[PDB]
Image (spheres, coloured by chain):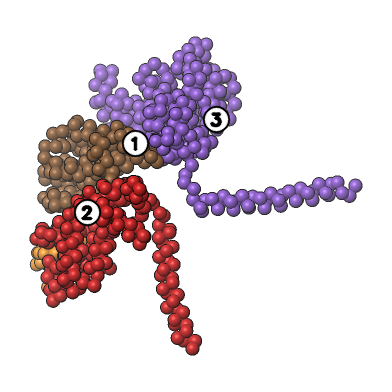
Chain colours: A orange, B red, C purple, D brown
Amino acid sequence: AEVKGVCTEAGMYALRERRVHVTQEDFEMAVAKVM
Amino acid sequence: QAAELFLDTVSTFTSYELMDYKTFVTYTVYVSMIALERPDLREKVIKGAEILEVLHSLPAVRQYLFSLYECRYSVFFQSLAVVEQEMKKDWLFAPHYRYYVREMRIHAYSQLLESYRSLTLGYMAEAFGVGVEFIDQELSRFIAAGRLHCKIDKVNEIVETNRPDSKNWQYQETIKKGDLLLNRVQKLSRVINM
Amino acid sequence: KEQNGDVKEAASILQELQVETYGSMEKKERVEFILEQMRLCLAVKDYIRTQIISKKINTKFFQEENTEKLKLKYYNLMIQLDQHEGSYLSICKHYRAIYDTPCIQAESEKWQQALKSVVLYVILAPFDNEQSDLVHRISGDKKLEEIPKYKDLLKLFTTMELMRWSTLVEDYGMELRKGSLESPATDVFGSTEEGEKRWKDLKNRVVEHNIRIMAKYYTRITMKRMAQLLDLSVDESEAFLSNLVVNKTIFAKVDRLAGIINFQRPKDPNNLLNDWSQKLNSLMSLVNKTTHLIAKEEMIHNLQ
Amino acid sequence: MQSGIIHAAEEKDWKTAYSYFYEAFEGYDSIDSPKAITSLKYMLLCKIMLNTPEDVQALVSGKLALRYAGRQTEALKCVAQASKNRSLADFEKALTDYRAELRDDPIISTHLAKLYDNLLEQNLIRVIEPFSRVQIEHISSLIKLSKADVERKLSQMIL
C-alpha cells in the first residue's frame, strides 16, 4: 500500500511541476513524503 | 502520424525489442523533418533535451537536421544523399526512400523560396551546390507536380514565387478525396444492388 | 507642522486619521478633514495617496445645501491631481462639476472661465464615445452663446470635416493661449511647461481629427497629400499614422514605395455579399413604403 | 530560490520558475531574511520572460510588493515597460540606466540575450505593422540596426 502511495505521490509531484512525465526526482520526493 | 507518435514517446521509449534508442531517435528526426512545420520542428526536435543529447551522440543526423533548420544548403544535400542510402538499406524505410527524398528536396526548395519574391536560378544553384541546369530541371519538375508555389522564367533565368490561397489547395484535396470515396461508394453500390 | 514647514510630517499626521470612520463627527468636518489630507498629500507630491484618499468622498454630498466651498476645493484638487497625472477627460468632468456650482454660476466671470476650461478640456480629450457624448452635451449647453469663440471651436471639433491647424491657430490661438484682456483667457495653454504640453496635445488632437475624417471619407490617399493636409512633413505624418495604427485607433495600410495610404480593409466576400443583401432588403422595404405612399395619394386624389 | 534559479538556468519552463520565485519571496518576505527584494527581482524577470510584461506593474504594486520600492524593482518596471512598448531602444536605455543592477551577472546576464532577441522580434513586428510595402532601409532607420541584420531577422521571422 505504501509503495502504491509512493507511485501516486510521484505522479502528483509530476503534476505539481506541470509536466507530462513522472521522473526520478518525482519518485524521490514521493518516497520522502510518504516516509 | 509516425512523427506525432515518435515525438510523444521520445522521452519514454523502452521498446528495445524493436530497435535501439539511437535508431529510434534517427527515425524520429527523419519523420519530424519530413512532417512537421518550422515552428513545431523548432519546439520539439531542435530543443527537446533527449533528442539533443542523442543527436550529440549521433554525428551525422544532427548535422542533417540542423542544416535543414538553419538553411545551410548543399550540406543538407550531402546529408540527404547519405540518409537516402541508409534509408534504402533499411527494411522499414526502403519502399519509401524515393518519396522521402523527393519530399525533403521539395521542402528545402519551398523553404528557400518562401522568403523571397524572386530568386535567380543561379542563386538557387549556388545555395544548393548543384548546377544551374540540374536545379532548373528539378524545380520545373516539382512545379509541374504542383508542390512548389512559384514559376521560373527561363529566357533570363529567375524563379518568381507566388502566394496561392489555401482555399485552392483545400478544394483540390477535397475533390481528390471525394473522388476516392465516391468511387468506393459506387463500387459498394454495384456490389449490393446486383 | 506645515506652518513650520516639514510638510511631509504634517501629511503623515493627517493620514494617520481614518476620518471616514468617525461617526460622531459631522459630515462637513469629515469632508474638510479629507480635503486637508488631499491637500497635504498633493504638497508632498504623493499622487497615488491623494487619489486613494479622494476615493473616500461621495460626490453626492456636494448637493445638500451649504456645500459650495467644499465642492469647489474638492474639484480643484481633483483638477490638480488629474493635471499632474495626464488625463483630460476627468479634468473636463471636474470643471463641468465646478460650472454646475451656484457660487461659480454667479459672478459672471467665474462661469466664463469655468466653461472655457470645460470646452478646452473636452477638446483636448482623445476621441471616444464618452468624449463624443460630452462634447454633444457641452455644445447643447445654451450659455455658450455668451462666449463667441469657444462655441465656434467646439463646432469645429464636432464638425465632420477637416480643419487646418494653421488657420485654427490664426483664428483662435491669439485668444486662447494669450490675449482676451476684456474676457480673461484661461490658463489651459498658458506659457508654462504644462501649457506647452497641453498645446502639443491639442495639435495631436487636431491631427487625430484630420486622420479620422480622411479615414472615413477616403478610399485611398497619398502620403505627400496626407502630410500636406495635416500640416506636418511626410515623416511626422507617417509616424503619427503608424502610432495610430499600432494603437489600433485607425486602420490604414501604407504602401511606402508608391507613397500611398489606403484606409479600406481588404475586401471580404462575406462583407461584400452582406452589403449587397442589406441593399436588397432596404430596396424591398423602400418599395413597400413607396407603394403605401401610392395608396395614400390614390386615396386622396381618386374618389374626387 | 535555488530551484527557481536552476530552472530557467536550464531554460525550458518559465512558469514553474516563476512559481518557485513566488514561493521563495513569500518565504523571504522579511520573515527570515532580506532577500525578498532579489526574489521579487527574479520573479519580475520570469514574468517578463513569459511574454507577459503587463503583470509586472501589478506584481510590484501589490500590497506586499509595495514596501520593496527601490532601484532593484524599478529597473524591472522599466524593462517591463520597454517590453510592453516593444521598443528595443527603450530596452537599451533601461539597461544603460540600470547597468550594474541588471548586468552585474545576478543570474540574468544569461537571459539578456533571449530578452534582446525576443524584444527585437516584437519591435520589428510593431514597426512593420502599419505597412503594406516598406523599404528595409526605412525599417533599419526606424529600429536602429544594420540593413543586413534586419534582412536576416526578417527572413527568419518569415520562415
Left/right placement of residue C159 relative to residue B178 reads right
Element assignment for label 1: loop
Name the kind of residue labelled 1 in the image: Gln
Left/right placement of residue C255 relative to residue B41 reads right
Circle 2 chain? B
Residue at 42% in and 33% down? C259
Tell me the distance, in whole angstroms, between the alpha carbons under discs 3 and 1.
33 Å
Label 2 neighbour load within 10 Å: few <14, some 14-19, many 20+: some
For the view shown, which residue lies furthest in the right direction? C304
Q: Quadrant of the N terminus of chain C?
A: top left
Q: Circle 2 sits on which residue?
A: B130
Residue contact between numbered discs 3 and 2, judged by CB atoms under 8 Å: no
Q: How many marks?
A: 3
Name the kind of residue labelled 3 in the image: Glu
Q: Circle 3 sits on which residue?
A: C161
Residue contact between numbered discs 3 and 1, judged by CB atoms under 8 Å: no
Which of the 4 quarters of the picture holds residue A31? bottom left
